[PDB]
Amino acid sequence: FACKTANGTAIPIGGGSANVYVNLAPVVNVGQNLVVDLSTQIFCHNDYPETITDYVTLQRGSAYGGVLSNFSGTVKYSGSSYPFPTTSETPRVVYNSRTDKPWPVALYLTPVSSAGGVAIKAGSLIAVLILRQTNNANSDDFQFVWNIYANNDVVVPT
Ligand SMILES: CCCCCCCO[C@H]1O[C@H](CO)[C@@H](O)[C@H](O)[C@@H]1O
Ligand code: NA
Image (cartoon, rainbow, N blue to C red):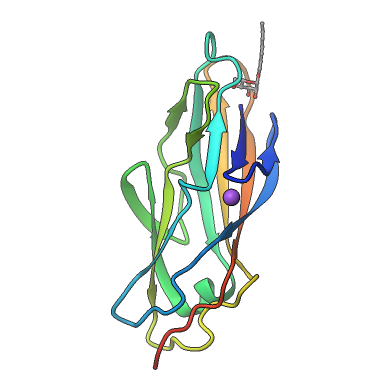
């Protein structure tokens, strides 16, 4: 089991960390949400699907930068909604092919009344998402750590 971003930045068997750079709507009013889909940019696969079933959770999601200070959030994982920042681990998604399959995570962020300016800074860390992988074969229990960076400034009009 290993993962990589859409541009091929990889985390190998056993886990580790990688950076993910996301485009963000450049102007978000206080009545709109800022949506950060990560499923189009984070992918994983199973290295021995003939035998092993891999199980993958969102173990934790933490907010940084302007997302932490200027937005409130939820995260959807595999079609279910949770608070963001998270409070506990989600249920599992199965990975059962050597072909890359998306990691089904997206953030839904709402400006808080204080927002703001600049609401999110280009190049800044905005989230850290921990993917936890186990299987039905052995003791492997690995963290894949995704550091999410904003590509661009986001302005919240006032
Ligand atoms: C004849 C025994 C072959 C043994 C191959 C084990 C490969 O293990 C790797 O790939 C497995 C399948 O993705 C993962 O469940 C495991 O955590 C690790 O990432
Ligand atoms: Na990418």
